[PDB]
Amino acid sequence: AQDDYRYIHFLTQHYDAKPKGRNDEYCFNMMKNRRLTRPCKDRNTFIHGNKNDIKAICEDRNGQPYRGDLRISKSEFQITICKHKGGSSRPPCRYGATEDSRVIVVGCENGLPVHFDESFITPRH
Image 1 (cartoon, helix red, strand yellow):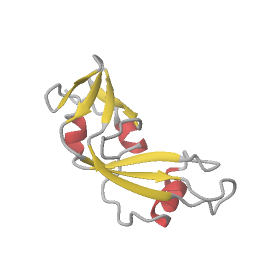
Image 2 (cartoon, helix red, strand yellow):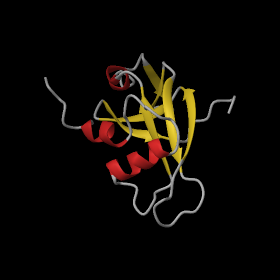
Image 3 (tube, helix red, strand yellow):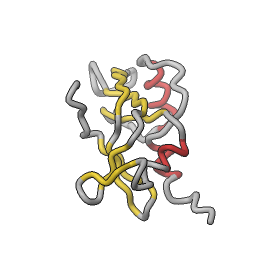
Image 4 (cartoon, helix red, strand yellow):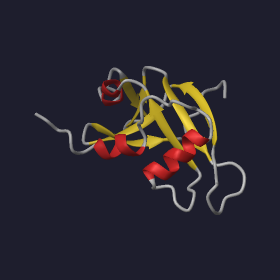
């Protein structure tokens, strides 16, 4: 069908793949690169994982319906949450990369995963 226009926006924003650095200057170089985080937008999750498996959170099986609209994934995805620590004004802002490795709640629009909830907590954290 080739419906690869819609959630490319989603996978630019959130999804990454290969955090080669899960540090601070990782997230600061992604602050500069992605540039939707000016003047230092604080929290922002990147997801790392298989790209086809992000797509297949909007199956129904491999991401089951949570709260009659939303999806909760099957697989634990890596999430590197660049969460801005320290002084929040001018660059160098830097970021507190707090990694979790957990199931994610996303939401689908159209039947493709568009939304990302950063609200989902595990009962471990």
